[PDB]
Image (cartoon, rainbow over all chains, first blue to last red; front, side, top):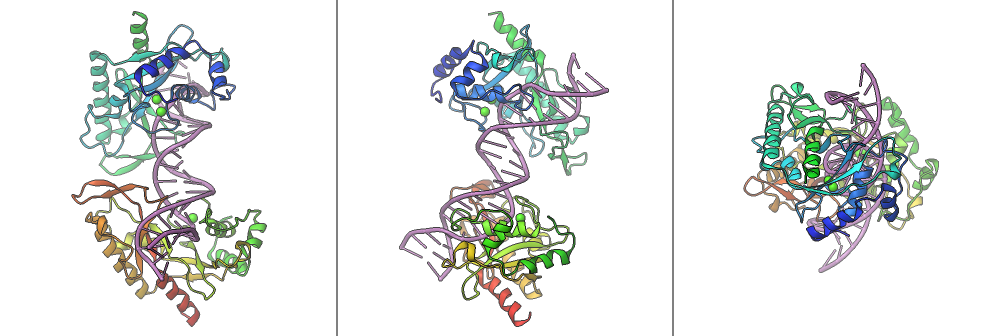
Amino acid sequence: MIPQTLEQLLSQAQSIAGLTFGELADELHIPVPIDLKRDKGWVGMLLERALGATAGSKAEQDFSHLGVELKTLPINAEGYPLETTFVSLAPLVQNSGVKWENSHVRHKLSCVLWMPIEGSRHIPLRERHIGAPIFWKPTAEQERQLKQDWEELMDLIVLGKLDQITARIGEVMQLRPKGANSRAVTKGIGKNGEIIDTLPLGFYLRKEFTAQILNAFLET
Amino acid sequence: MIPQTLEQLLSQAQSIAGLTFGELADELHIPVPIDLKRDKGWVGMLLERALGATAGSKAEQDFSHLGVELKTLPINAEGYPLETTFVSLAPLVQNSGVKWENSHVRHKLSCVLWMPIEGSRHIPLRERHIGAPIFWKPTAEQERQLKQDWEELMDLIVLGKLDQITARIGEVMQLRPKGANSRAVTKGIGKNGEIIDTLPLGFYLRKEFTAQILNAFLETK
DNA sequence: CAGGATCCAAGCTTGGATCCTG
DNA sequence: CAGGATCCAAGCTTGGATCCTG
Ligand SMILES: [Ca+2]
Ligand SMILES: [Ca+2]
Ligand SMILES: [Ca+2]
Ligand SMILES: [Ca+2]
């Protein structure tokens, strides 16, 4: 079930490539919803089960004994990312003199097993296909880009400049809301340093960034 | 649902006095377990339902708008508390130089609606009676005793001396574990002032203290 | 188009407490 | 005896993400 080897995980990943959500859900005796409107994480959770990841786990990475993070990536009919990719929650407090090297973002993006999946709305959920895995490590350039955005976004957060934060900041990674709705709150830092109530935020990779990953892969 | 005034809450409390757990649960269409081994907070939830408090709620007081905390108190055949009373989780971190005046314990114990309930093991759960409420405010003496224990206990906590803490400390209030089991953990302060993983502790009123409240209630105090 | 808003699963934490072994 | 250990229910929070106006 849970792969004990990196070779095991990749082979298990190679083997589900080409399957439709219906076929895989069938094997795992997992019911398939009509669509993702009220099961937004169903596909990500489907792949976790098929690959041996623990459901609901809060570990730094899906496979801590391998140092591998698993992420599904919805792609459109032309091979382009359909959505941005959620990475992790931005620490709004207890962010003192935090460095990039020890960041959650870095930890989660150091080694990613990308599982591209069809996301086109015109295709019935049951029939969407699972693509071929892409075992990824950020290039020296990609990591410099991520680090730069992380530092810029974090400076904004640590300085209580949350009001100035928009999704438009960041070259390849951005901050957008991450919660139940626009009324969700978590502790943050105000304009004077007081601990305030604020909208929880998460780091997201932009579509251009993941599109670059898919492109480099195709070029191989 | 939620009482809007104090006379409403108190009249309702006085009206359920004398009912057995079975009669109350039946009224509420709530199933009654065989015993409390795997339903330790069942009686407490039962009273919350009957008095309009909210289930699952994590507010400081059960009835914040009224400034009242609801607490069942198990009593034996002779009228003596059967167990200590849980008050609240002791804050093991970010405890800085907080004072008793604005502590959770003081707040929670500023006004308590005690609902004594039969707890004798020889009485089938369904047949146990709910007693008459005791609407209590600590006397200067009681508050003084609590405050003293609170500070002595909080000192051990704030100075990273959790290793030294046992339930034997405190005159009327003590610290005992509070969690799933002895493997439960929450953040605390270690010997070097660093944040560590440690057993979650809770403030409990000793049986002598709640007994005092009951005794004072009978005497006419 | 895509920034801001929104939804589910399940582990985690808290509040309700009583249990149980020398 | 009673200190140390333990158990349920229900919010709360986090990891999985896609939805949806203007
Ligand atoms: Ca996971
Ligand atoms: Ca993952
Ligand atoms: Ca309550
Ligand atoms: Ca209560």
